[PDB]
Amino acid sequence: GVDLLGFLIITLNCNVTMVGKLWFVLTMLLRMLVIVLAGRPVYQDEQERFVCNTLQPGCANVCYDVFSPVSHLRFWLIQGVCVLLPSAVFSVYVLHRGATLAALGPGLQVPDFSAGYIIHLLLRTLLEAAFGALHYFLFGFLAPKKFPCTRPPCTGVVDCYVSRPTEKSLLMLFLWAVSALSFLLGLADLVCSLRRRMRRR
Amino acid sequence: GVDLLGFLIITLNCNVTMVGKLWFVLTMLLRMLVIVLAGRPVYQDEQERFVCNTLQPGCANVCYDVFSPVSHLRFWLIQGVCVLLPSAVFSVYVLHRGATLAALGPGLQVPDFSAGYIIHLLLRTLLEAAFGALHYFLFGFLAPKKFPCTRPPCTGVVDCYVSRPTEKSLLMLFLWAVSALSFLLGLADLVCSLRRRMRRR
Amino acid sequence: GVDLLGFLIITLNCNVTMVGKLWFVLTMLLRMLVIVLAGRPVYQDEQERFVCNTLQPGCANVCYDVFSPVSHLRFWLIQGVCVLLPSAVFSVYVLHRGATLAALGPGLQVPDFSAGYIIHLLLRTLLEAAFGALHYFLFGFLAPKKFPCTRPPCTGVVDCYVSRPTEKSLLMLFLWAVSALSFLLGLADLVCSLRRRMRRR
Amino acid sequence: GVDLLGFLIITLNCNVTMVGKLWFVLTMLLRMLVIVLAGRPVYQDEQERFVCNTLQPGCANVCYDVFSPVSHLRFWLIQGVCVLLPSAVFSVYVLHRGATLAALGPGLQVPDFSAGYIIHLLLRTLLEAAFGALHYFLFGFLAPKKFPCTRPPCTGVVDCYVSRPTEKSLLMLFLWAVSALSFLLGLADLVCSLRRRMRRR
Amino acid sequence: GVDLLGFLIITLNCNVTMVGKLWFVLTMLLRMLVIVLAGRPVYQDEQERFVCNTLQPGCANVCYDVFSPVSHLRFWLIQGVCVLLPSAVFSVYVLHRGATLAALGPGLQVPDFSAGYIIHLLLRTLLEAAFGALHYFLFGFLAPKKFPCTRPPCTGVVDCYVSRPTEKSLLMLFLWAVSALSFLLGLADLVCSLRRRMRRR
Amino acid sequence: GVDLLGFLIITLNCNVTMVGKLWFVLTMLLRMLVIVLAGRPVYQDEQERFVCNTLQPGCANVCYDVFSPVSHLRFWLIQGVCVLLPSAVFSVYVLHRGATLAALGPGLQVPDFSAGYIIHLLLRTLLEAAFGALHYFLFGFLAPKKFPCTRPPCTGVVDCYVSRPTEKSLLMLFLWAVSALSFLLGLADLVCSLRRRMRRR
Amino acid sequence: GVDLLGFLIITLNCNVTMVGKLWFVLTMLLRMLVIVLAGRPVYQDEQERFVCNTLQPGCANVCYDVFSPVSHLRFWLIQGVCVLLPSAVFSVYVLHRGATLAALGPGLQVPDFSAGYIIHLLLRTLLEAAFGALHYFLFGFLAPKKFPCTRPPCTGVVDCYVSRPTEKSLLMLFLWAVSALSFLLGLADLVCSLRRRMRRR
Amino acid sequence: GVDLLGFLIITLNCNVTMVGKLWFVLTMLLRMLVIVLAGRPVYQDEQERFVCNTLQPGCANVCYDVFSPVSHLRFWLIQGVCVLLPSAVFSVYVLHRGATLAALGPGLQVPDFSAGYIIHLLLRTLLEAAFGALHYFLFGFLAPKKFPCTRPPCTGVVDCYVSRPTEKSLLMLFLWAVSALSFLLGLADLVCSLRRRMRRR
Amino acid sequence: GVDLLGFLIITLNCNVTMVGKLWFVLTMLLRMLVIVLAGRPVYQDEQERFVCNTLQPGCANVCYDVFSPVSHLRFWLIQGVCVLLPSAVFSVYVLHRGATLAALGPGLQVPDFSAGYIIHLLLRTLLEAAFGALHYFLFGFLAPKKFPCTRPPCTGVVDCYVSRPTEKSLLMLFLWAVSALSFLLGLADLVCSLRRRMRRR
Amino acid sequence: GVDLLGFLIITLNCNVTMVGKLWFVLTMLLRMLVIVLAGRPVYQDEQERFVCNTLQPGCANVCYDVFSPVSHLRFWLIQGVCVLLPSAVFSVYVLHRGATLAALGPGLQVPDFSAGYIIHLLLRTLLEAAFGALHYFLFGFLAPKKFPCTRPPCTGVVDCYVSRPTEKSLLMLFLWAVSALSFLLGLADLVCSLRRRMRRR
């Protein structure tokens, strides 16, 4: 005998473990917040000071074009949105299937949404290692300090200087560390959740 | 016997299919979020480095003016707001017609708002293909790398260089792909919803 | 016999017509959202490239000062905040007068807040035409392409070039069109609401 | 016999007058919104175009350093946060003391939080006049147009030009006017509230 | 006999003291708001005007690289997120343990979450002094005005000028003061909370 | 049981709203008083100093005759008397119908004179806009400074000078403003009075 | 059982019809007020600018003396005072005969003063047509523009110019119209009052 | 048993005859009103156009000084105030002696103030004939048209012309007639009042 | 047992003697009325005809400026307002103290306001002799007929003529006489009132 | 048990202090009376004798136009009407709220209108200092004696003379003094009235 703003969140909380909520909090507070708030200003001047010894117009632009095909800030943001998408689609799924059964009607009668959470965590584990592999094969571990440029709309080889490398290396090391921690915690979620459901058998 | 914060969301959820909620989630998380967050910084320096071989003041500005009449970032934002508007007007419609009947009063009595959802999806299908056609006829598929400029407040023809083309081409390809996916999913919504309502006949 | 999170929104919805909610949605989604999101980036480089033929320092700054006394972006924002203020003051008024009567207590007993909505719409109609007249008398319809400058801290007359005019003209035409549509819809609201209240007599 | 999401807002609304809510609305809609949204873009180019007649590097920077010790945008923001802080601390106080008494339990029994609101308004009146006095003694009424610079890391006296003064003067006049209106309205709140409580005696 | 949107916030408010809520308000209104809103614009031009007497390209960039290894804005943001993280993890913990017991069911029966709040405050006290020590040992109290640069990709020693130091010194003094106040208030919370729980013995 | 100098003014006050009395006060203190007291002396010397270059007698008189057909002072006075007439005729009506019923005789028995007040306000609203339109089409907004005169009892074209124009323009602007304020307030009276009488139904 | 400030005005109002009060209001507000307030200033400069071609002193004065024997302003004022005199003498009569009977003393006992009101209206009708006839035979309908003067203290015939004729013609037309309206209304009063007294027979 | 705003006017009306009230009305409506309203404007230009054949400065002023020692307008006003003074002093006397006896207290008990009214009328009759005699001996019956001037600050005899004589003669004839009528009516008052008081003997 | 429009004027009349009322009547009818009505027109042409033998512009104006520093008309008006002010302040005092005691409530109970009337008459006697002394020392008894002028913006000594002196001398003699009569009567009031109050002892 | 012409003025007198009535008397007798009666005649000839050395027609008029933009007589009158307006609006307010409660009915029951009088005096204090500041910044303390004129419709610089300056300076000094006295007395009213109402607490 509860209102449906009542038996609508227990059907949400009971199907998710506290480790999952902790994962959500860590990946929204230290992962979704640092990138927009600190990564946005640092990478604005990646264009302004790609300064290096040439004089004919149009060498520096092609030098940076061959230098940075894809900035890793966009990589981080797309990785973040894809690693947050399934938690939203599952949220919509569970709210949709919880708000519908109460309309028909009949010490609670909480439904058991266990089949989708394990496949959810499987998709989580699969969607992190691959993007980590792409990060490792594309951007490495530490950013270069200088770059030789040879594709000529300009005469000769131009030795061209990046702007502010140490900040970038430290910040991306921090992102690597937090991503590694999240990966292990996510692996812990599934391996604990599967055991805590066959124990009833 | 439920509160009106009760029989106010089932009258919302029951008239919309889970495919529609999934559409909403995908077009707000991968479509409304990427554009503001990643498209805003990339296109700030479309003006700073339209660099090219001229010396008299006032050639580069007219060269860009003849180069880019309308930036496609504004096109994407206006397309996004117009493709999100009907879902808001229908939301207001259904809340208005659900919160009013409960005032008069008389195992639920959920109203059937099916006539408006099919015309809603018709408007959705009509409002996407046209803007896609304008995108195709105006901005093409890949951005040029260099541009010849001839309208003289300046002497001669000026070969003028864009800034950072590959990032733009990849990003707009991603937008094209997500828009194509959303179009097919939206076509699926109406064609399934119409069948699931004549089946009762 | 409803909770006071119950008989608190019907006393809000019943005193406002669906045309009013549609007005609110259109003026927050296509009017409050486009200006902050697309008008902010376009007008950052109104200062950087006011480029024109002079060499002594301090001519370009006074030339722009005599050029643009007030930027119309600030005009649009102040117009938006003033055209959204009365809907907030009325909202606070109606919530205050609805949450107070329920404390004393005694098939609903919804109060009739009709006197304030008609004067609300009168204030709406009065607060739009005047600012439209100021817009017409101050900023015209299309932005100039070049400007002659004569006030001397610099020698001679300087012919000075604006940056990116066509984008500005198209965007402000779009704002003019949406404002005109909102004006007519707002005029429709009052003229329909007054009739729908004397019909009971 | 009401839920505690019930007797939790009347204990909030009944202890505050409609003039106070109107004050809150005016100081968040015309005061907190204009500053972030219009004051942020105008003052970005206060650094870019502090242009003036010198050639040795490092004169303009010290000239601006002696020119503007503290920008008044930061002054406005700190003033805004301090003039909004007490309304938040009182809000937390009243919610804390309202949500606690209902736990013990026993035509309502609304508590009377009148002692704190009068001291609240006293603190309000005291925290505005002082900062107004600092504003008057530090930033004056109208911004200069040109500035003489003498502290030498550079040779001679440099006559140095500000950027866009009239916009700044008009905007800060608008802030002065709205602050003056808020001050008088806040003085009205306390002087009316004290009378409306001794009238019961 | 209350709804579970009822006995869900008293189980939140009763386990936290009003001093804690005041701490939350002060550290989100004067600490989380000033940094994003005033610290973001001031530190954008820390790169643009690191101006100083050299002519060969690539001396200024390495001079700033040896000048500022880590900007203290990022230090402040990471400190803020780490000093707000435990209050979020505890919030999730208490909501999770409060929303679960109500499902089973049986003048209230509020649980006593006192063990976690004291260890929470211990972690708070430990996570502030260390970062304060790092701040003191890394960034000092006042920012320099000029800097000698010697690491050669450039010929000689370059005396290089910072931009806008007094604003930075005053602002970081304000942050130091508010952090010191928060530290003392947080120390007060634990020392009062421990006493107010052994008094029942 | 009251004297008839008693139940003779409540039958007057009860049928008129406080907004109406405020209208009466504003239009007699700032409208009937300024015109007689300040407009009478200013316009005496509109004849004495219509001075201009001619020598044959009888050119200046015909020049002013073609210059000013009707002085706007008389227009203002006739407008004032016509906008005060209905309030006098209604006053006489209500006193006549109140002093007569008491002669016959039978916690008061105040009559309801509501039908005449609404038609009174209708006549008010109709009798202001028309005269405003005549004012706009006849006297414009600002008075000329000089006038060419051609109708010959005199030789040639005579350029003829008005006396004291700025005082006249400012004063008539003040009258325009007060008339505009009175118009809006009068429109408010009827629209509020009609609502406050159907609310009883 | 009423005070004598009571049964002293009903004995005044009951013997006069509402048409009579309306006549009084119209002839004091549009007839007694316009003449003193607008007719006084216009006719001050009827003497100053009776300008015309002569040079020997003392021709213009005799020319005006033969021009205007009696100014029609004095005619209007004497007509007004004579058309207001009987209403005052009757007022004094009725107050005198009402305040005297109450001294002796004995659902009212209002006296019937009907014989004097009909003779009053007869005197009214007789005292208007005659003065209208004198106005028509003396001052005509429109004022001349120029006047020939022949009575010699001066040599020759002098063609002499009036000042401001159109204002005078329009104003006296307005007086003619209001007088005509008052005449018809006064004729209506008697013809209705005589019928409404023989109807009782 | 009447209020003292009751037995305060019958003690005023009963001691004065209707002929006296008629005298008051005629001498305030046709005597006090014509002089201020029509005599004030006519006599303003008695100074401006005392025009006559002389050229040396200062002859015309002495010519008028010997012409008009005292203007008869001031004579009329002083005569009016002296002929209205006793009616005011008697009014104050009777109100003072009527408002005092009622304080002590005891089908009315009206006092008999007959002794003062007869001496009042005696003073009236005495204060009119003398001033009439002065008028006759000083100002005659008709005003001259021209005047010879001989007292030399100027050379010769100057024949000097008055302005507008016929208006003055007609107006002062009207005053003479009304004064003569008032004199006879006042003589009638006393001779009737004395008889109507010895008839009781 | 009287109404409060009853025991409100006896408390006014009983505290003032008939000599005082006679003083009020004489000083308002022969003193306040003559000055506004006859002194206003006579002194308008004190400026127009200050005619005298000079030709260079700007001698006559300075000659009158040295002639009349202060016109005695303004002196008379300020003297009148100051000699009428205390009678108004005492009137307000006595009405205020009479209308207040009746609110509380308990062959009359008239209060005795004798202390203020004697000090009132003392202030009267003191405020007349001083202004009479200033009149005597400033304006003398008879006005000059001609004036020598020497302060040069003009060449030589100019013998300059006043306008209409005899009227002024006679009129100001009349004012002197009436003021002298009022002074003696006012001295009589106090000396009689003090005796008529110690006689009760 | 009093008539309603009874309990209608005590509800007026009791809510206003004797200092307020004294203020009303002083500002209507020495402030409203001097300006109309003495300021009207003095400033009529501000136009007639603006005499100065020029001969071409149309120089003097423009010279005065640049001389006096706004005459301070109109400033004084508008200041007077605005400083008398609130006392009228409050009067109407209190009579309206006093005459209405008596209709319903139930050693008096006088209402307490204290809240409006303090805000009334606040508005009084605010509406005087500002207009005093405008007076000080616009018209100064003493009027000039001569004025140089340069705006050419006339040849050269014209030294132009005012008329009667010392009278103007003395009179406006008197107005300044009386305004200063009224300001201090009004400040006394509020500061005494606020104390005399918290003394009851």
Image (tube, coloured by chain):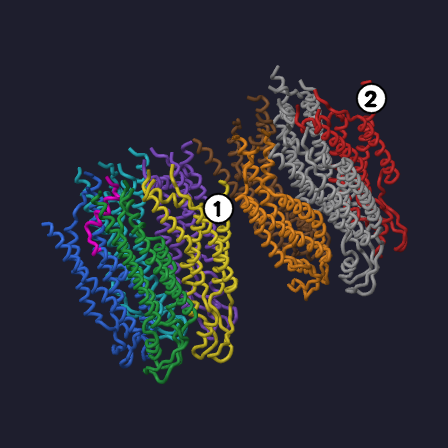
Chain colours: A blue, B cyan, C purple, D yellow, E green, F brown, H red, J orange
Crowdedness near tag 2: few (<14), some (14–19) or many (≥20) residues, C-alpha within 10 Å: few
Magenta-span inclusion, residue A3: yes
Q: Decide if residue C77 is in sight here.
A: no
- What residue is shown with label 2? H195
Is disc 1 placed on a helix, strand or loop? helix
* Prevailing secondary structure of the magenta residues: loop
Q: Quadrant of residue H76?
A: top right
Q: Where residue D34 sits in the image (x, y, percent)?
A: 43, 57
Q: Residue at x 19, y 67 (%)?
A: A134
Crowdedness near tag 1: few (<14), some (14–19) or many (≥20) residues, C-alpha within 10 Å: some
Outermost front residue: E201
Q: Where residue C106 sits in the image (x, y, percent)?
A: 38, 34
Is disc 2 placed on a helix, strand or loop? helix
Are the residues flagged by discs 2 and 1 from a single subunit? no
User: Is residue C54 placed above or below H183 in the rendered structure?
Assistant: below
Q: Which residues are magenta?
A: A1-20
Q: Nearer the viewer, residue A43 or E117?
A: E117
**Label 1 sits on what residue type?**
Ser
Tell us which disc is closer to us: 2 or 1.
Answer: 1
- The answer to whether J7 appears left or right of E118 in the picture is right
- The answer to whether B178 appears left or right of D155 in the picture is left
Say which mark, if any, is on residue D193.
Answer: 1
